[PDB]
Picture 1 (cartoon, rainbow, N blue to C red):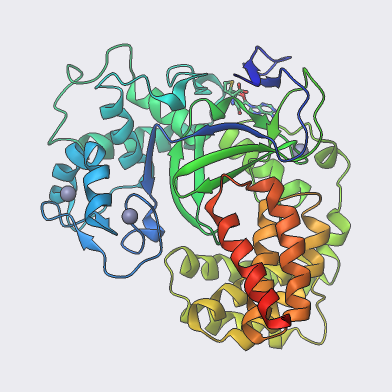
Picture 2 (picture 1 turned 60 degrees about the vertical axis):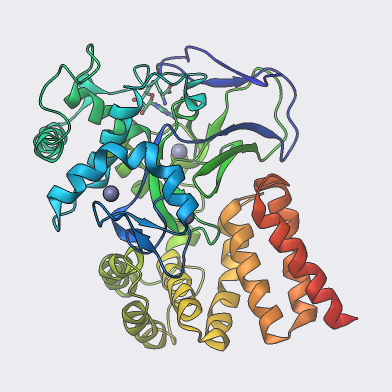
Length: 424
Ligand SMILES: Nc1ncnc2c1ncn2[C@@H]1O[C@H](CSCC[C@H](N)C(=O)O)[C@@H](O)[C@H]1O
Ligand SMILES: [Zn+2]
Ligand SMILES: [Zn+2]
Ligand SMILES: [Zn+2]
């Protein structure tokens, strides 16, 4: 029994709208990807399937590239890894770009003929390409891949015979770039990327009515606010820690459009975001580029090296409420956590609590998780009174964003009751 529908929008291709009244936290759609892969960063640190930060990863006997959590995970992924395994062995040790490997996976999937439940609303051939509205460096970037693609797929693909006809590579990639989704783990860390054709119908907003969470590679679409019938459905395409400017910039450079959202048009919260001295945070912003490099690759130690310096450096001057300051804290935290310096972790993250409340308005999965992490630490620290507070708060947020359908709730409840037992 369905709850939404496809339609041609005002001026922007297609889109998605409701067909019933929808309350907060309602589960609207649910999909496995059509194709997905572990992104370069997390490669060789999470499983090419369940996508989970783990112990002892056995690597495909054949290619010796793909890594797997269990013997079952390996077996399950095999339908996909089947063909690529070959090429990955030839690339060794040169490893192909995510978007390339991803495409390989979509090629093969369209070459079995499975009525993929991810395409139930919009096929792959229906996806926007923006061919006519692309720049030149962009177009020249695309021809790049096609070349790198064909060298990579030498082993399995010799010519357009083995491709589904009415199918252009150059075109395909265009679809990829603006139709891809960043997959995150429980701790809202980016671990892989995939295409979710039915979900791609959702359009952008900087203050949207819908969220997406990932239970491993499995995607959940939920409502976040009360929605009246016939209303267009939107998610945010971006991180919420950006300025009206930054947002516009990427959207042009990646999706090829100018934003409509109220917020974009009236520089919403932009003052607060940049509150402070430009000269300080102009340097801070720069350092972060090299820092986040060492985050996607899980270099932790090295990130903390850089982080701790800057927070102690501009401790006298720059407030927590500034985004760049905050971003550092956020990192400083995720560092200490993966290092074990939990006392330190807490001391930091606890300071991100207030800014987050402000920047992540309503019910946002990121805020929830953050709160959870912070409460979880307090619980570890034995600050049960303050812990119970956040855990509850976090629950109250996540009961909307995740639902009983996401396994992380099961884990959060258990934390609540454990905290309970220490208040006995
Ligand atoms: N909020 C928004 N404002 C303007 N254009 C948008 C948008 N969200 C998506 N688009 C554009 O819609 C075009 C594709 S039309 C087909 C899929 C698309 N996501 C859709 O809206 O149906 C793309 O150029 C994409 O950037
Ligand atoms: Zn292999
Ligand atoms: Zn696994
Ligand atoms: Zn906007």
